[PDB]
Image 1 (spheres, each protein chain N blue to C red):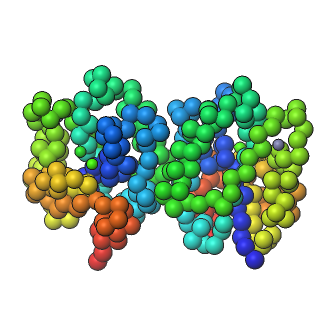
Image 2: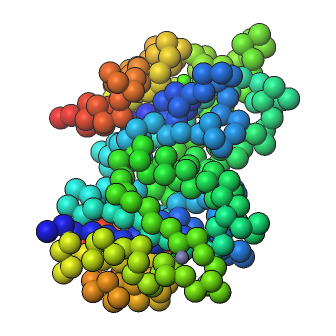
Image 3: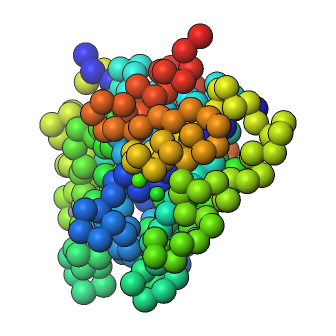
Length: 163
Length: 158
Ligand SMILES: [Ca+2]
Ligand SMILES: [Ca+2]
Ligand SMILES: [Cl-]
Ligand SMILES: [Cl-]
Ligand SMILES: [Zn+2]
Ligand SMILES: [Zn+2]
C-alpha cells in the first residue's frame, strides 16, 4: 500500500507569509492543479494522509475557530471533488513546547511505521519545507519537495504515476 | 464554431443555501460533487464555459456586494487555480419585482453569443435555466445532484 503524506500550508494551499496561519477565509487559496492531480494519484492506487504543523492552534495566538472555518471548507472542497484523506494529522504545538508530534518527528504517523503497514519503497512525504523532507527520512520513505514552479502538482502527478 | 456551456451558479456549481438562497457567508460555500474534474474534462473536449446567475437583490441591504464578493471570489479562486476558466461571469442583480431586461430566462446577458447552437448547452437546476436554453435556441440540461449530476454530464457530453 503506497501512501502520500502530504503537508498542508504551502503545499495543498498557499502559506500566508505574514503569520503562516490560514486563520481567515481570505487567506485560503488552493495550490495550482492540486485537486485534479490528487484525483489522478488516487486513481493510480495512492492513499492520502494529511500532516501539518499548526503552531499554537487552539490557543489565542491561533484560535481553533479561526482555523476551523477555512480548514473545513478546504476539506469540503476536497471531499466533494473526490479527494479523500485517510487521516488529517495535526501538531498544534509551538516549537518551544518540544512536543513529540511536531514534524519531522514521526509520532503522528507511528501506525504507518508498523512493519507491514505500508510500501516504504513507493510511499512519499510531499511538502514544501526541509522538515517535510526530514520527516520522509525519519519515516524511512521518499521525500518530495513541493515547489509551485519547479516541482508542482502536475509534475508530481506525472512523476508518481510513471511506469 | 464554438461549443459553449452556459452554467448556472447557485445549485449547479455550488450548493444553494436552503433557507435564504444567497451565498452571503463563507460558511455557506460548498462545491457540487465532481464539478471540478468534470468541468476540466469538459474543457478538454472543447467546451468553453460561461457562468450565468440571477442574484436577487445583489447590492441591496438584503444582499450587500461585500457579502457576495467574499464567497464568490473564493469560489473563483478555487476554479481558476484548478484549471477551470469561465470566459465570463454574467450576473443579473435584480429582484424579480424590478422586471428587468436581464433576469434569466431572458436572453440579454447573453445577446453577444446569440456559437455551435447544436452542441451548446444551458446547465442549471431550475426550470428557468431550461427556459433560458429554449430562448437561446440551444440545449438544456437540468442539473440535479442526485439524478443528473456532474459525472453524468461530463460523460454525456464527451
Ligand atoms: Ca508547509
Ligand atoms: Ca440555480
Ligand atoms: Cl508543517
Ligand atoms: Cl439563477
Ligand atoms: Zn506537537
Ligand atoms: Zn436583471
